[PDB]
Image (cartoon, rainbow, N blue to C red; front, side):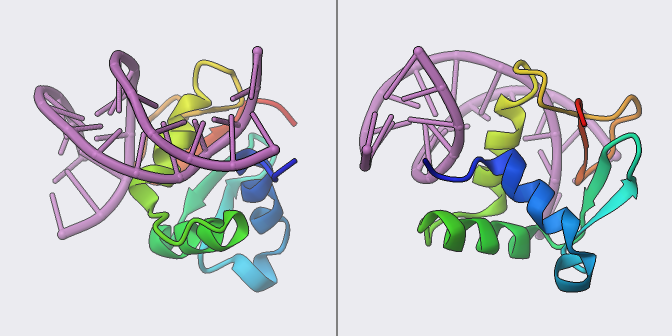
Amino acid sequence: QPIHLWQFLKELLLKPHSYGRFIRWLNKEKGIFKIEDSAQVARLWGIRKNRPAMNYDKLSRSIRQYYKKGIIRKPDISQRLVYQFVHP
DNA sequence: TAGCAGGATGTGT
DNA sequence: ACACATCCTGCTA
């Protein structure tokens, strides 16, 4: 079973030493993160899944599919490149 | 420019 | 079934 996108995102967020210039917690407790380097996050996701055509347009389309699943959501005050984990 | 909401359909297990 | 990936239009900062 391939890694899921939400888990992949949590993985990058776990190690700011390695990935902090690409993606970071804005509010760790509330699960609010910012994508700082969208092209880079998409590039890393494409490598992980072996989709060399992956880009942020398509990565973010998959994040949006999470809205109705209650996995990721946009924060109360919506901001570009800012997202929020619903649970843990 | 670049990101964002969500439909339709292709891909691979 | 499931989780995307890949196309799309229209919308928004």
